[PDB]
Image: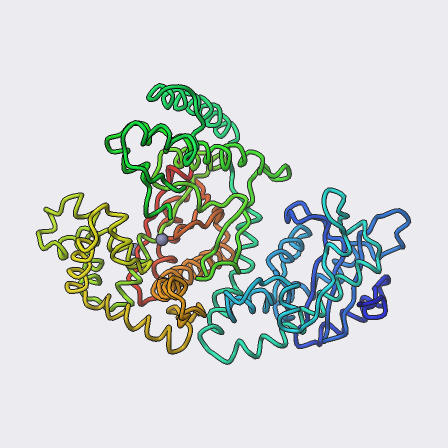
Length: 601
Ligand SMILES: [Zn+2]
Ligand SMILES: [Zn+2]
């Protein structure tokens, strides 16, 4: 175990002050906030734990209120004594997911500064795909030490105790060990992080500074109109009933909208070709092929889609409105993607259909408060611009340089015809190629997306590579370093480790290769987006203008800008994003505004 002998439980000021004194002279120290909820904005601080060095940690319980809880330093007293240390930018702190702790202290008017090391981000930058980056996994992985699990002290299910109900000493064991272990983890990882300037730069200048900005974005939240969302729900229910009647009307009898069961016995039994359509999917969708002529597969397609959308955003979103703010606070994950892109949950902003009407109606529900407007700043096809840069292709670079539509320019070159005359089919073909390249898509895969025969796709690809040599070179040079060094990195040095690069297995290695070509571009976009956030947030914090960065989805940053400041701010956001980030990639930021996210979008 870990007993009560390990860490002191600070129950008096004198001892707290003694610790604060020791904390002031420690080179770095790890600390944790303990609370009664995961919901940052409404969580209450139950106590704090600090680690001055390995083995020396303490828990200061401030709000444990179970039956007969012993006297504790009051939260306010503890916080006013601790405040100076926490706010001192010179006092360097280490923590596991400091984003969370920074937010909790903010609930008390304390501005956590000195957010120097986050063991979570250390782990993530060391090797994003090494496994899970939570304390329990880290402690075991790096220290062969199994930390006291939260469940161990709190329990499970509905009857799980909140921290304030847990006995002082038990709470002590958990909090102090966590603080202790975080410090040890940092001590093991920090040295490693310096063995390579790449990862080091990323962690230092990209990940770490992003911590307080993510906290700020999450705590600000986004205004969602529940009324609009409910109307949408109602309408969707009517559309589902209607589409369902239309389904039955096209065939005979009633049936679920489930393939490999009901649809095949109808569709192919009424003429068509036997294979169904898996919902794999983004390569062979038999249902939408038939849709250009066959009516039934067309309605089943739209029905399921609307069904998915309704339950996920229409029915859920209103439930996510925080009673304390009356806003939705999405949870961004800084250490989850293999590439380094921020992901999002509750809600997963990225799964809201972009090119679809219903998705648009969802975005319409993301509204600007009175006298404010939504401002969307998007990096126009940044990944394609990155690829142009990475491949040093003058063709692509020039296309972007002279503001031409690369998909049309690509088509103009691949199919050899004037830019003004490239047709939508050709532009769409060049587009399938362009984006196919980012994901390292095989010629056969491109054919499946373009509905053209194999080798016809290959014909297009050979013609591309001939007209755009740099891209092939890039692809080859990337697959090359991938095998030689087992990893690929972004312009900022962010690394993605490809263990199955020499897999000796087929598809597993193939995957590693697609990842090899893709990650540098996707990862670089991530890096850029993160630097834009830091840059923008810095201006926000310094100049204090009437604007809130409320979202980050894909390559766009979304704000709430005061209507009277829109222009000045629009200019400023724009310059910050396409000028105060990397200066090597030809970047373009499309800024838009409107009454809601869909409008600015
Ligand atoms: Zn993008
Ligand atoms: Zn510009």
